[PDB]
Length: 79
Image 1 (cartoon, one colour):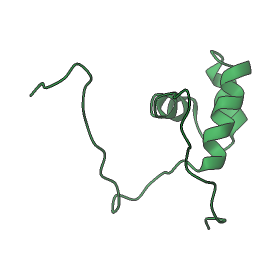
Image 2: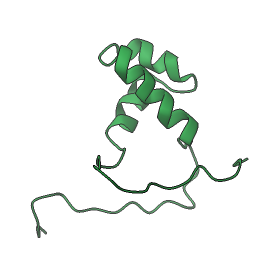
Image 3: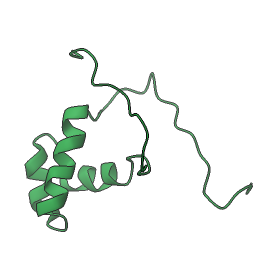
Image 4: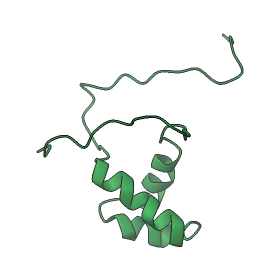
């Protein structure tokens, strides 16, 4: 089924337990993406609790870049 150019899709997560990227991690990934942009081996190390593979994936997950749009707030300290 094809409607538009972009591959429309939705992700439903709630019960499936496993791994999760925390706002903290998300940033780390970027920090390295600047220095070890290509050097994945290091990237996986920069983060801390992530492997080369995982890192690569996460990278292809983040939302689209916007010119001007108020993003969510850090909020409380999620435990």
